[PDB]
Figure 1: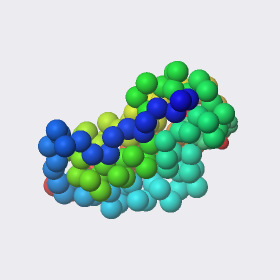
Figure 2: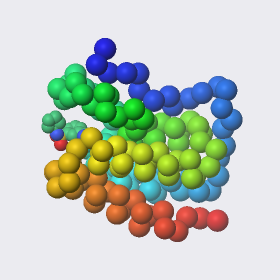
Figure 3: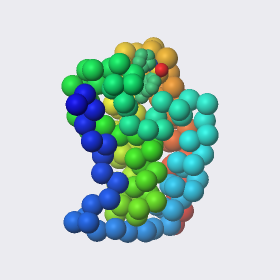
Figure 4: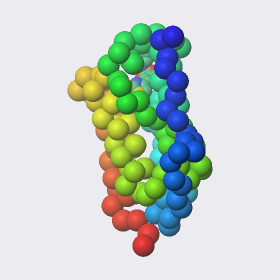
Length: 125
Ligand SMILES: O=c1[nH]c(-c2cccc(S(=O)(=O)NC3CCCC3)c2)cs1
């Protein structure tokens, strides 16, 4: 298939954790970013069949999206906030990698990344 399986949202071999920072990342950061006018392309894994992007997964080897991140947070999949933040950063970077400077989708990622950074600048203790 053109589409690989989506990234795991559970892994019984991996330990779970809940922290105040992870709770914040779900309740405030993700759930607020989700409502942004530019969030829609990033709310689910890229579907290469739907979007007619047969090269997407030929180029992007560590796919990530906010749907996956949300499920991971809901599952307590992450050990800590930094692990979650790394997934957001992978999502943004993938967008810059797959596309070109100035592309509409890149302008969307750039705006979301700024909002994301604003929100994670300060996390709860
Ligand atoms: O690099 C990435 N592109 C996307 C994406 C997902 C759904 C739609 C779009 S888009 O802005 O509507 N571009 C269309 C995608 C195929 C041709 C145009 C981008 C998520 S991550």
